[PDB]
Image (cartoon, rainbow, N blue to C red):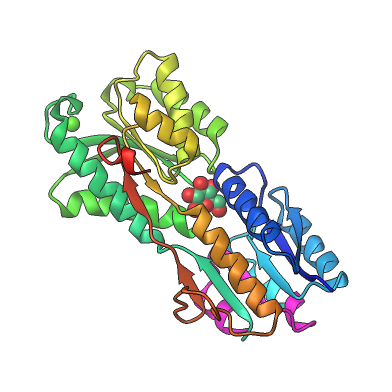
Amino acid sequence: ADTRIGVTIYKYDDNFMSVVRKAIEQDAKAAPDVQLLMNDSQNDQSKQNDQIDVLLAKGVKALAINLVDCAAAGTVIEKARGQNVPVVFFNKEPSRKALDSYDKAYYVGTDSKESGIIQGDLIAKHWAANQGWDLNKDGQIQFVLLKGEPCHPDAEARTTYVIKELNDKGIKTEQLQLDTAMWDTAQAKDKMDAWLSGPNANKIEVVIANNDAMAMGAVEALKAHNKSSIPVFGVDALPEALALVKSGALAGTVLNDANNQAKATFDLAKNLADGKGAADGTNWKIDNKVVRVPYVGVDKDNLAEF
Ligand SMILES: OC[C@H]1O[C@@H](O)[C@H](O)[C@@H](O)[C@@H]1O
Ligand SMILES: [Ca+2]
């Protein structure tokens, strides 16, 4: 009797997707006529592909798919199409072409560039309020940047737009180091430690991370080098990160609204499973099959709101 919805999470121990997956499990458990079949793809698209085959064998009436491979939507769509099963992609955004190739494909996520713009504005505000951060007193921000996984739309947009926004405001920037840490805390700690062991160590004025997990790794490397005075900025507003905004270990972040992305994903998947319009009975705004949930800047000054 219960409507089965298959869900794949690209990697369960991704800090942000852990918040999302626990929220969507809660949403489903609050709803009686639904059974969620949850899968950890263990950061391997081949594993996810096999999981989708199994979910289809089990007759799920909708799929909610958080891709491993940024470009794998077409592969997933062709599996789903064979059984007329709708697919709500979430958090890793397929191409416009992929979404348009299947009348039952949808996406729930964010306007990726917005998070870069907000982060840049946040840095600009704090830079202006903390001119002691300009260690070499040249009027430019000497920064290092910890990038997410290449090709992930959030990594690409946050990396491009944080710097564009600063520069557009009239703040010149100098990139001292930039590398991916693949969204991961331990990789970011190791990378930041390398940078703090290299010739630019002393010159680094601001650490910019594409997410909070990498920001937290940087914070722990700075602590080990007795350089916690160097500001670090993140994205996601993870609970662990907000505690660092409060303690002063993290200068700022940006809410990536996991609870509403989870709810929208669930709501659309359940409507589609039921053969209804994707947004029926909800306030979600679907624009060409996409729901985007706003980001919100967070620092000590507005922390009491969160
Ligand atoms: O796809 C996973 C990534 O999604 C991004 O939107 C989040 O900001 C990251 O923390 C996360 O690692
Ligand atoms: Ca400077």
Q: Is residue 123 above or below residue 28?
A: above
Q: Is residue 196 above or below residue 92?
A: above
Left or right side of 40 for 26 = left
Left or right side of 293 for 10 = right
Stretch in magenta: 79-102
- In the rendered image, the quadrant that contains the C terminus is top left
Residue at position x 27%, y 48% in the image: 120
Q: Is residue 252 above or below residue 63?
A: above
Residue at position x 48%, y 38% in the image: 239
Residue at position x 72%, y 48% in the image: 42
Could one spot residue 150 in this view of the protein? no
Q: In the rendering, at what x and y percent does residue 54 appear?
A: 85, 65
Q: In the rendering, at what x and y percent does residue 5 appear?
A: 74, 68
Q: Is residue 92 magenta?
A: yes
Residue situated in front as seen by the camera: 55 or 155: 55
Q: In the rendering, at what x and y percent does residue 62 appear?
A: 72, 73
- In the rendered image, the quadrant that contains the N terminus is bottom right
